[PDB]
Image (spheres, coloured by chain):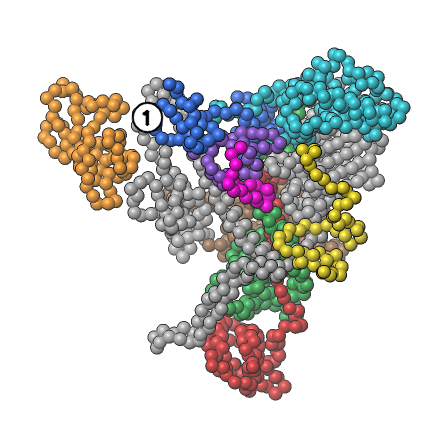
Chain colours: A green, B red, C yellow, D brown, E cyan, F orange, H purple, I blue
Amino acid sequence: MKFKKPPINNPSDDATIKLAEAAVSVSDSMLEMAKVEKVITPPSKDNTLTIPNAYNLQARASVDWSGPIEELTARIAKAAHFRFRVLGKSPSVPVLISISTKDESLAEILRDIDYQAGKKASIHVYPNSQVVELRYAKIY
Amino acid sequence: KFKKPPINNPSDDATIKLAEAAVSVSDSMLEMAKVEKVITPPSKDNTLTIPNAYNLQARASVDWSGPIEELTARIAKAAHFRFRVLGKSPSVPVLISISTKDESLAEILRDIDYQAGKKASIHVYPNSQVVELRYAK
Amino acid sequence: AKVEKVITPPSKDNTLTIPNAYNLQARASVDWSGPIEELTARIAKAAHFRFRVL
Amino acid sequence: VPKLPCRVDGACDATIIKMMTDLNKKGIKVASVGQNYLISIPASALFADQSPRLNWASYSLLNEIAAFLKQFRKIAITVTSYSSKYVSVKRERALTLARSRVVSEYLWSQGVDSRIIFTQGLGSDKPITSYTLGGDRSPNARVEITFRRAV
Amino acid sequence: VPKLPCRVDGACDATIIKMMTDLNKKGIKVASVGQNYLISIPASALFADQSPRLNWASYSLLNEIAAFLKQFRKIAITVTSYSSKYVSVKRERALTLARSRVVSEYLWSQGVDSRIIFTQGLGSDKPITSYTLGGDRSPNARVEITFRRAV
Amino acid sequence: IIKTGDIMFAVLDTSVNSDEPGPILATIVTGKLKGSKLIGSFNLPSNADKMVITFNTMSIPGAEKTISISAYAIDPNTARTALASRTN
Amino acid sequence: CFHPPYNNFQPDRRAVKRVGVDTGGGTVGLVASIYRDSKRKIIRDLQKQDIQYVEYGDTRTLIIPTDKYFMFSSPRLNEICYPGLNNVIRLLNFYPQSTIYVAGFTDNVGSRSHKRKLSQAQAETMMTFLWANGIAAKRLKAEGYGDKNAISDNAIIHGSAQNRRIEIQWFTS
Amino acid sequence: MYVRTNLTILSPGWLASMTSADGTHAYEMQKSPVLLVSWHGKVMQLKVEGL
Amino acid sequence: DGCCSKMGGINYCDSSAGRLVCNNGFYSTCYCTRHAVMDLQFLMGCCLWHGGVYPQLNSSGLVVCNDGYVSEECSLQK
Amino acid sequence: DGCCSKMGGINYCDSSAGRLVCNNGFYSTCYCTRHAVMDLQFLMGCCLWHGGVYPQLNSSGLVVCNDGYVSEECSLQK
Amino acid sequence: MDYVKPEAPNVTLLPKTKAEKEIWCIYTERGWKNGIDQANTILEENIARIKEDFGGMILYRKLLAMNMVSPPYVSHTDLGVTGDGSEIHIDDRVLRITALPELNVNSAEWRAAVAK
């Protein structure tokens, strides 16, 4: 007959509380700015065409990387048994990507990577030659 | 017998909120990058293709930082291809840095074209074994 | 306050009512500050209507 | 120097060779050459008959596997699965893929400090013997993990 | 800070849970969901047969539920009633409305710390029992009060 | 600014008998001036009821200066002027 | 014996092992078995656990915490509270004619479509587990709502922790 | 005095005030040891010392 | 003294609520932080509804507030 | 203390890795140089993420950073 | 937050009675509480500061999408080989921003938003 309420956990901490109370407004701001950006510009194309899937891309990978692109892409090409190609010249300021995913396709990881690159580097794959090429953009 | 819980698991009410907030901001920035990245189809790309003739299959370790005309002249002499130009040289030449330890000549030419960009390009004809360096206007 | 308050009849309210055409039944989350012309042109294009000004 | 670590925490070579000898007497093979190390495990103690579903008693085995794994330093861990020819190629490849996915997911749930986890299976493509008498009782139906100790 | 009260005035959680347990043993429905509490009383213990006249001894129970409600901080309480169908629809609608008015007026005379008391009466519009042989002796002849414990 | 007649602490670590006057050093341990050293002397009382220290020459580290604020001693944790020693 | 994976969805004979280890008395084993399968002891066990059962009127309801019963941000299920799951199916075996509704609820933060899809997936996997326990699909309705009707408040951390939930409702007839 | 909150002051009167996107208010005004606000339709006092 | 008494006891204090969250799933009536909802209906302090007491050291017993209003009631009489 | 226990003992310190190497064929756990890869994730000191502490002493009790920031937790007060 | 742990306790006047020992203990406890509050205050102010900067950057991005702020404009000047007979630089590029971003006054170029 003793009363209770279900959701009970370990006791929390006030700094985490204040972190949550900041992060909710940060996430809300991100949500509305992403919505207004999606409205204010209609997309037309996706990197599915530039990076088409093929065989031996089904080997899954879970990652936590926080460095430059090139070592990570070298490990990817080593696991993928595909030839490596680099175009353009490396800039002075390095390009650093933090990725924390869970067991996705290699093609989707690569599409995430080029989306992270944006307008600095681009990714192409030639399955006719079993190669993967990255290119630094012409800039300044 | 014993199945352990995850070690650094979000077992706290603040931590799960922080985690889903992280998921939200990551998804927002992901679709921002998706809607903002601009590409071209791989049929409309204006890059030099690979003629894949047998003379281009040689390998080299080449480091260079300077002009392009003498460079592709040396490449054509190494490939036993005749070489010519098409246009007039600008006052400031286009300087291309190359650093490779092992590469073949066709993709060497492809990255040369990629570094050249809009100001010049290269055509390679394997019917009569020639190359030309075409300027812009 | 009852005697000094003024009001308007609900029959003679000079507010444009809802014509309830089916293109007008959509929802939006919109914040805007400023002029009126871009707002009415954008909501006209959202409504897929023609537009005019007098 | 007292403000610096004398040794990396959670590391003791006597315990390393102790659990290495325990796994050797258990039967799971541990191969060490240069610095790249391989662990070969039979699948019969891990799963049921041709199924991508674990056993309850294998959780302590996975626990001590992760205890061995958190001991070292790494960058990438590669896990691959192998089976026997049963009906087709596709079913067996999917079975090995599911087993590799499950073991990689549980290992990431455990506190290994890897940066990259690669998971895949092959089925019955590269047998370690021509002794094709057994199915799930054959020693070639297996799972192998591979990594390299860094620095 | 000693001038600041450690707890809110006139409250003790042990007293609250004790009188809540006593009232649940007395036989009235107490429900807690999140921070929202709702109390249901059978009307046969409160009124006469289909009439808005009050049993005189029931004001002790009214004082008890007033003392229980004194321990909480709130703004809005919904007071409604339900009944059986006797002759019409309007009869029990007016009866439930008037009984809600009576109990809300006495509660407002007593020590309510809220700001809004809502009075509605519907009668026999939402039955909650498959059993329908009783009239006022049915459990559907009832009153209820809902609120949220705010902050 | 140090106010006219406030409190500070020091530590005495080098001993002397009250026979020949000379420099004696203490080190201020807390407060505004940190790492400071103070040299001074003592006086000879004709009566054996107490013993006090004449401290005059102060040095503050960091800046190479020498001010000469003069101050005396009190017995710690008794707040008296006596010296904890033998008089027999 | 027994299997912590739900005893492979097999109907557990709890009485025979208890009366065997008690006869190793028969009467005290029988009264212990009826004490174990007695509904009030099951309800007190569910009160010892973090799952809320309410009976009032013709409707009976169950409230299940998503955080303590699932892995985070996933329709996959926690594999620890399976004694709670076994007691859930043991209690729900008593009423083989009521229609069953299950619903999911989440808090206020995130994409609206994400909240709706997450709650729908959680309700669907819960009703899938219930269907696998033996009850046919004609009595089952799964709905996943987001922040439509909050049982708690989101401006308080503890209330927001209380907010996400699993609701089970069933009538009498 | 500069006060950031979400409530609305009653007693002293402020020279300026600002409204956020979330309805939180900021007030710039003269100093005071006390404030009066309405929280949820209920009046309340507030004390600030060390002016 | 006993906030979650005859209960599971104290779990923690939520400063989002400024309240003692008990081991049982209900907030206690006790506050922890000063940033909580304490309904204040009576207070202390001289020179109220002013700028506070003017901080000069008047030689006479007459006192004034920072707004200029004279709080002779708070001041000693003569 | 004991690094190469249950082994052949410590053979030598390889400074290219900065680590000990035991008398078996394997690398050890302990290190010998400070130019190695230790995962230092806890630090002390004040005026961090700034220009460092100010080397010139302060007449007052406050402490400024070389960036110009004030380290309040490194500053004492009453 | 910075962290210099002090491990130097010095006593001015030692406690002799249990009453003065008790008031010393509770005043030490109250000072412990005060230091806790000050740490929370500093943390909260820094939280507000970094949230302010993040909100300012994301509001700049959102207002640029709202077409109220000019983008920055930056020119490039490239030169080939340069230097004396002792020093050479193969290609130098000098990048210089010439037009800082700013808000506009002409209201007509402001595209609003819509949603579904």
Residue F52 versus residue B3 in the image, above or below:
above
Q: Quadrant of residue G151?
A: top right
Residue B2 or E41: which is nearer the viewer? E41
In the image as oriented, which residue stretches furthest toward the front? C4
The structure residue drawn at horizontal position 62% and vertical position 65%, both measured from the top left corner, is B38
Q: Quadrant of the C terminus of chain B?
A: bottom right
Q: Residue at x 66, y 58 (%)?
A: C38
E3 on left or right of K64: left
Measured from the top left, where is residue E57 in percent x and y? 74, 12
In the foreground, B77 or H49: H49
Badge 1 element? loop
- Residue K58 vs E44, above or below: the answer is below
* Residue G137 picture location, percent across and down: 82, 41
Which of the two residues, D76 or K36, is positioned nearer the viewer here? K36
Q: Is residue A85 above or below residue K57?
A: below
Residue type at mark 1: give it: Ser
At horizontal 21% and vertical 40% (from top left) the residue drawn is F59
Q: Which is nearer the eye, B55 or D127?
A: B55
Q: Give, as a single range, the part of the protein colored magenta.
A: H11-27
Q: Residue furthest right?
A: E87
The residue under label 1 is I59
Based on the picture, tell me whether residue H23 belongs to the magenta stretch: yes
Mark 1 nearby-residue class (10 Å; few <14, some 14–19, many ≥20): few
Query: Is residue B2 among what the camera can see?
Result: no
- Relative to G92, does residue A29 appear above or below in the rendering? below
Where residue D30 sits: x, y (%)?
56, 50
Direction from residue G113 to residue K72 in the image, left or right = left
